[PDB]
């Protein structure tokens, strides 16, 4: 699979993160990210995708050692961690055809797994509008514990 790069943007308090809402197959909330072009560097893909989806340029903020990276069905996804962005920042997707909304969310109130259906005696997971973000929440919390306390 083709690797994807993007960003976990936090506010000044480290309480809140920035999520984007897609359409159709991407109909819930996730971190801004996308597939890398041929010969494009990780950090440049990250800045490009985040800019298309939020109107915020992260080029001069990226720390090349500061990221979280997961494999998800044999696709690599790396999100660079960008702390200290004020909540009064104007965001503005370029691609209005891809992005329905942008909003800040409380990290402690976000879920880190989806719920089962054992109250109903049925296998699988109940739907969750944070499906795309969920895998990154627990790594993010641990990474923040370590780097800050
Ligand atoms: C929209 C856009 C196109 C592109 O190819 O690269 C970008 C980069 C990366 N460097 C500067 C080339 C940005 O930092 C910010 C925006 C873009």
Image: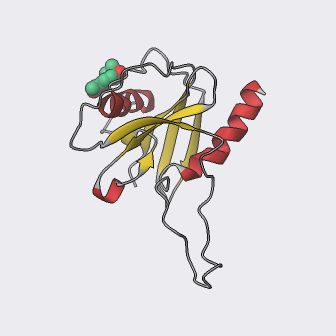
Q: Position of residue 95 (x, y in %)?
A: 23, 36
Q: Where residue 125 sits in the image (x, y, percent)?
A: 55, 71
Q: Is residue 94 visible?
A: yes
Q: Residue furthest top?
A: 60
x, y (%) of residue 29? 43, 48
Q: Residue at x 26, y 44 (%)?
A: 98
> Which quadrant: the C terminus?
top right
The percent position of residue 131, horizontal first and vertical second, equals: 49, 56
Instruction: Residue at 66%, 47% (x, y): give it.
Output: 138
The image quadrant where one finds the N terminus is bottom left
Look at 49% across and 45% down and name the residue there: 77
Q: Is residue 57 left or right of residue 87?
A: left
**Camera-side residue of 83 and 12:** 12
The image quadrant that residue 113 belongs to is bottom right
Question: Nearest the camera: 77 or 102?
Answer: 102
Give residue 60's quadrant in the image.
top left
Residue at (42, 43) in percent of width and height: 4
């Amino acid at each position: 699979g083709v690797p994807t790069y993007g960003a976990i943007i936090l506010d000044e308090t480290l309480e809140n993160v920035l999520l984007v809402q897609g359409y159709l197959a991407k109909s819930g909330w996730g971190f801004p990210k996308g597939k890398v072009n041929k010969e494009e560097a990780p950090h440049d893909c990250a800045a490009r995708e985040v800019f298309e989806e939020t109107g915020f340029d992260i080029k001069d903020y990226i720390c090349k050692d500061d990221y979280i990276e997961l494999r998800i069905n044999d696709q690599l996804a790396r999100l660079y961690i960008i702390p200290g962005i004020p909540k009064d920042t104007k965001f503005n997707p370029k691609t209005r055809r891809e992005i329905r909304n942008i909003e800040w969310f409380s990290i402690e109130k976000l879920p880190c797994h989806r719920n089962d259906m054992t109250p109903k005696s049925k296998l699988g997971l109940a739907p969750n509008k944070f499906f795309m973000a969920i895998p990154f929440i627990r790594p993010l919390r641990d990474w923040l514990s370590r780097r800050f306390g």
